[PDB]
Image (cartoon, coloured by chain):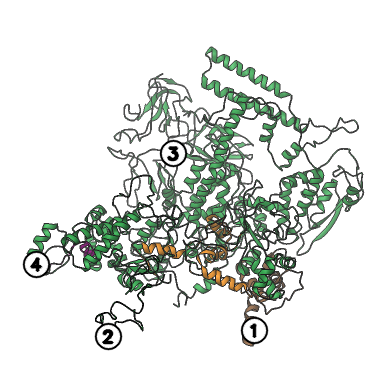
Amino acid sequence: EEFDAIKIALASPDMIRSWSFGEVKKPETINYRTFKPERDXXXXXXXXXXXXXXXXXXXXXXXXXXXXXXXXXXXXXXXXXXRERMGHIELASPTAHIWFLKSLPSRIGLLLDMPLRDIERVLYFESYVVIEGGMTNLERQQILTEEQYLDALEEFGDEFDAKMGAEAIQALLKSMDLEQECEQLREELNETNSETKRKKLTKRIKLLEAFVQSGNKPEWMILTVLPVLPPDLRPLVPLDGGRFATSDLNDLYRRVINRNNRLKRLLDLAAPDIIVRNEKRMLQEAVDALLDNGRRGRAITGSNKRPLKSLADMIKGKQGRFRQNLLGKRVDYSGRSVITVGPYLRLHQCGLPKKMALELFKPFIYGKLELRGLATTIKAAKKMVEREEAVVWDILDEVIREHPVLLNRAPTLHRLGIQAFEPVLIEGKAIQLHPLVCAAYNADFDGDQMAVHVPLTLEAQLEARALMMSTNNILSPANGEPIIVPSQDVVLGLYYMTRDCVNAKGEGMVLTGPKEAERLYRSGLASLHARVKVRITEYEKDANGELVAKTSLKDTTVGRAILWMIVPKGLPYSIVNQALGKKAISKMLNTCYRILGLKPTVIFADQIMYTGFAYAARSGASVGIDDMVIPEKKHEIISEAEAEVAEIQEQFQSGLVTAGERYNKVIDIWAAANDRVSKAMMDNLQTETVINRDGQEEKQVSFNSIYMMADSGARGSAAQIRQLAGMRGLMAKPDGSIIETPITANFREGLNVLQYFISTHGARKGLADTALKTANSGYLTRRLVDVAQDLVVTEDDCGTHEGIMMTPVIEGGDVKEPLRDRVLGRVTAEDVLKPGTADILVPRNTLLHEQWCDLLEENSVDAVKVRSVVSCDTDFGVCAHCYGRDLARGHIINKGEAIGVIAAQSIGEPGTQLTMRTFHIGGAASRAAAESSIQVKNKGSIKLSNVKSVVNSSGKLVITSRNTELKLIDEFGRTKESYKVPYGAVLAKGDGEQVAGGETVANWDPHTMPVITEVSGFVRFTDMIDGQTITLSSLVVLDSAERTAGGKDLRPALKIVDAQGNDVLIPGTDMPAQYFLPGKAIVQLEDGVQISSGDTLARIPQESGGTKDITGGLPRVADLFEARRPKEPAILAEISGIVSFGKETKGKRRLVITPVDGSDPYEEMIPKWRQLNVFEGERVERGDVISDGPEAPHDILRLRGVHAVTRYIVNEVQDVYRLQGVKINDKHIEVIVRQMLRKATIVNAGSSDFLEGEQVEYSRVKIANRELEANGKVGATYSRDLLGITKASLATESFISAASFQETTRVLTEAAVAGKRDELRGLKENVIVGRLIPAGTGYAYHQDRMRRRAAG
Amino acid sequence: HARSTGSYSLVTQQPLGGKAQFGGQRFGEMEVWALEAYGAAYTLQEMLTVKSDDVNGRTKMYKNIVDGNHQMEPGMPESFNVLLKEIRSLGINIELE
Amino acid sequence: ARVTVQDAVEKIGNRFDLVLVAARRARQMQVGGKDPLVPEENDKTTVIALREIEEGLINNQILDVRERQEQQEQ
């Protein structure tokens, strides 16, 4: 019996009159000074019985009864209360016409077939348009002028129906016939169809069908009575603390008050043309001017508040209604503390203080004294608390121990920002917080504030107890690895713990297990000693459900023996479990967490921290003047570099060297010299530090704290240390180029004044950038999270056959990531590893053990078909089994989880939170492996995939096609390194040979294209038009975009000729010697110039195709998340068949398409920007790119496919954030792609939805019920174009939601006509309406409770 | 400054903010998406509603503190009634069925 | 105190409704009318409910049969 959503409807006189029923009655209560309101009710003393003006005694004459009652003082009889129901008063009865036509589309304009501006003019104007009639031949909508209305009324006489003002607008809105217009325009546009007809006609037909089947009458658009709110519901937020001032609300109050009151009394009084004209124009501007237009002639211009423009300040405070609802409120129960760090107690617990305690626990203290009975009444307990008795502290502790507290930092990013801890009292005003958790919050101790909230009872305390606990949530659904930061004194302390030293004291020790207590704590045994024979017991978990012990003597240092006592469970026992005390401690933490992720794996794992800060504090590392080491080679390197640069400026003084090459050269010498100072700095960081023992010649490992931080990894970096001792580097914020005045002074040495000047310059620029990235990252999270709201994730496994082929990235010299991490933890349709022997079966899940077994054994196959989230047969929501299994908790996730929605939306936050270096790193570096010299990873046979090998006469090898592939295959067959081989690359060995690590097959200069030819001879320009296409004198061949449309069909090419005139073809190739020149290229040698074998002709100064280099980190992040198609597309092949290019184009798009032969052809032209990759002498299949460059989102979605889209997006994102240092799994990114590819357009016909696109799920239901029905031909295909994906928030099927994320006025205007009910399917709409989110924990009650919707 | 319950405002029934010895500070849209991120429907749904936009949630909540019924009323948000309100002042007025 | 809920997840993995189940048991013991079946570490009835779920003798069917048994006997 619970209500469902709301009802979108219009303003009607019956419902609004129901909201009033009293018309407009009285001020109610106020005006105490006045002493009386309007005072017309029934009483024992009414003095007006049996009539209106008569007495009960029959003596109403003289001075008795009548208007005078029993009390002639104050207190009126009219009140009408204040809050229960929204009232209504007159408030501009005749017209409204405000929020229709307010949006860019005019709704009354399309229903009345009238333009916007003409509606704005004809309102408050004379109107006079005729309405229906049987005696008149004029149209129902036929509009007349004043005089035409006088002659029409005096001529036609009776049966002529028209009204004085807005009534003819009221009367057209009333007289519009939706059925006759629907069938009339339906049969008319269906009988006569045109390209211009479908627009504004067909959509008008379906739109009028939406009006007819909507149920709301257009007559309800206008309001006869306007419902007025009670102040509490009315309330307006004043800017000045609540002042009304001069605003157009007050202007329209002064004009609309007198004009509206005089208009009501005039209309009810049948006023003449003077008062009805002045009151009709003044009131018409009162109701109409507040709606639209008007002149802001308010008080004096300037020095006055004018918070009225579109009258949108009521619906939208700043960006919308967010401030009122759908955004963050002031919450409750908050300490608002500042973080302190407790090292002690438990990873999850709170050093909640006594002062913050008992302030928010007052209800639990009152109920505690009640149930326990130490108090008598609630007031007595209040006295006990206000008196601050000592007994209250004991029961207070009884409550606090197991009553958790949830914690969050105000700038919240990801899901782990809020975590539940078990509070314990600590004396102080602050909260001691676990430092390993501080890195999870990202919070710092610089004094950033803290929001402390108290959960409420069952769902909050226990939900945060079984979910949001910091130990219960370890894994981070962004990187995928468990996020723990045992850095700082844990890395330094474990580094000092695990290490060796020559000689020193103690030598070896026979004692083994308990050698730390007696040996360490007694005397004579250092914390670390090399060559100790102490044995270490081992445990083997390979047995089923049982551990197999073992023991043996291993050489290990005393500190390593101390670290071994931390984890009693099975370990590598000082091999991988000790190492150097580096991030490998986090690695062994991961391997220890790999088995039984609950359990003493979880608990007592903090002993690494207790011993870390314990024996780190015992170590007591320190930094001082002696700590840093200045290399003596610095003087020789700075002097030599200064001498070389002195020779450079001497050559520039002589004029032999240009200023540019001299500047960049000097930059190179100071850069390489700074590298030399860094390397010598490091050399003196390890081998210069010595320890004197006995002869001291052997010395020992360095104990320097700087080296412990650099090698250990607790903090600092080789670059920061390079600034501490070596050169600081060079940068210029205003110029953007490396300065020619380097900093030769170390921090220990006195810096120069100008050095400090440039350093604080660039440092200020760094502060500006790092301060700028926060807002941009926040806005990115705004867009992404606004898109991600749509994930229900309901069905478990729908058994879909579609899955992505999994192949490694294998880019550059070394592979960036292995395929095992991508294929790990993903459902697998087939996924046959090895040469198809057996491998996995069809119905088998991929775990870490099975995927690790197939990855380690028979690794020759790196490609396996794995199901992905983007491809799911589930109609509504996503399938957890198809998406994958992982979470902050253990594996095997369940339904109702946001998954990649919020996990990915929060995953993209840390990547864009900080740029990498100057942000040009994430951009196009313009220098790549295959771009300069193609290199191989593993020794093996290098082959060219999808290419035609063309041998030349010089012995080299060139690719005949445009887009090629160059891969290095090992003896097993697995792909090592594969890069796309572009046309024009001359390689020593095309195929059949081998290559080693770091082998370069071909070398091409990226600055100038060599365009190496084959047969020697004179250069001849082929298909080069002077003055139209193409324009020391050297020719310039530009792109066909700037070429004349007449000669743009042909393309310029360099054709070599012999001395006799005959053409000599290349050996083994049917085509002769020539080179295809792309756009923007420059040809140096002109006609009539002899050339030898392999002579250059033209070079590409710029790429031209997809020209523009790299947008940058922010532009590529907001562009990729923006999902919009590329600026300049290239070409694609939709269907298979004979592919050819022929004929020409005259005054149109160049390069008409000879192909499409076979199945019915269509002539395909184009501007011909990028070079054509496809060959004209061969038949092309479906899905082959006919040109290089970007494939665009639409052509890549309908051509390249979902798989190629996922490859592009995942590869680009993981490369950018990979160079940034953040490795993000494929799952969440493919969820972003899943939400990007939804709402694909639909071409289907016969299902209705004619010619217009609809949702993909609607196509699954329409085609499902289609093939289910006896007619299967009704279903058709659909285009995969993803639009811009930034309007997907506007494309949500829900009503109330996204209205706050978008413009409230525009959403209300556009959707309010469509009249679709929200239905509470939107999650954020549920957040606004108050009913629980049908996901997460509430998915059970929403599924079982919402499962009764079919019953009614 | 620690605060539990305090003065509210006549606008939307939300309290003013800090420095008033009232209010829970603020958990903004980032915390809304943090509860949507943790997947807790309870904390968010009763968050936006019970504390401010709902008097029923506070009255029934404090009444449930006695004997510890522990239930919190989901309620109909009065701030959502400020949105419905403002829309009612707008020329297109929406009414529930 | 309970180290990790993952043990009760090993009992019956859900994690979606375990909030409502353990909140129902901790509701029965917190409101009154129910007694702890586990020796107390001084942990409150909520953690006693977590260990009750870890015991294996409390689940959805036990709350349904026991709830209908108390409703029929009352």
Precedes in sequence: disc 3 or disc 4: 4
The x, y position of residue A449, in whole percent, is 62, 51
Circle nearer the viewer, 4 or 2: 2
Report the residue at 29% width, 86% height from top: A56
The residue labelled by disc 1 is C70
Identified at 29% across, 38% down, the residue is: A1145
Colour orange belongs to chain: B
Residue on which disc 3 sits? A1106
Q: Does the residue at mark 4 contact the one at mark 2 (Cβ under 8 Å)? A: no
**Do the residues indicated by labels 4 and 2 lie within the same chain of the protein?**
yes
Q: Among the chains, which one is green?
A: A
**Disc 4/disc 2 C-alpha distance (Å):** 47 Å
- Chain bearing mark 4: A
Cα distance between the residues tagged 3 and 4: 71 Å
Residue segment shown in magenta = A155-173
Q: Is mark 2 on a helix, strand or loop?
A: loop
For the residues labelled 3 and 2, the Cα–Cα distance comes to 93 Å
- The amino acid type of the residue labelled 1 equals Glu
User: Percent from the top left, x then y, of residue A132?
Assistant: 16, 67
Considering the image in quadrants, where does the N terminus of chain B appear? bottom right
Quarter of the view holding residue A864 = bottom right
Residue A50: mark in rendering: 2
**Mark 1 burial class by Cα count in 10 Å: few <14, some 14-19, many 20+:** few
Of the image marks 3 and 2, the number of the one nearer the N terminus: 2
